[PDB]
Length: 291
RNA sequence: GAAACAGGGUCAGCUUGCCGUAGGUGGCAUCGCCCUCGUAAAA
Image (tube, protein in one colour):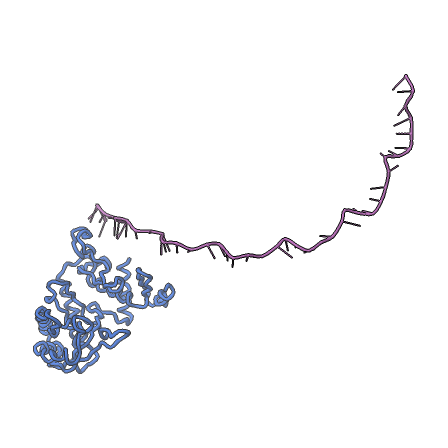
């Protein structure tokens, strides 16, 4: 009942003010956010990096998912608004600026289609004009704040537009409904059965969402990657069919648990710990008592 | 839901006195004493 249980807990977190990502997001940490007006052009640069024992990568913002780069044609894929410096600002960082430019090229296009698919939000218009006039930040990326010089702890920056100061353009309502309906449409495009978890016919998710914490590297919960494990011609990640919506559900539930206090990580075997009726008052304890 | 290695090896070694010494001693009557006796045996 592994995956089904994970899904149960995701449902609990969603329904119980747990503030988990809503089917359409990941709580990616933004090292710093560019504050913009209707034209941006470096209205301000806030650095969010101020955090715990180390100078971390910002405040936890349930921004759209990391669409993942996966190497070769990295620049083609670009996260929705929050993204890599070369994608967003076309900051050089190194000779890998040309690719960054291409990164920027697609990121712009992404933002541009974000404007085209979702107009009437000042944020996307703002970032579009921002991309047009990134020179205003071409100085700022060495004027206000820095990216720790290769691709580290300043990378994965994002955009916040002035006049709200607390809500990221990524997590802005308008952009949110866009990304949710987009996750719905692209899902509708793909095949439609069957969930291993909800058991309903639903979009099968290739590339399970790489839950983070058990391995040192964030790792797939279940990714039939190598060719042999590819069992019955389902051939990569359909080998296991799980509803992509439910894929999100459980992978986020697992991520939260793995990052929650419930991680009594005995040596290798990290051990999350649910409660079907969440908050059974033992869930928080179960690590403290076995660890 | 077939085919699938825990694997290919890895001195516990190297070496180290249980020793240097250390009275069983000093010493203490076997004693004090006691009839083999009373006796029957020259065929």
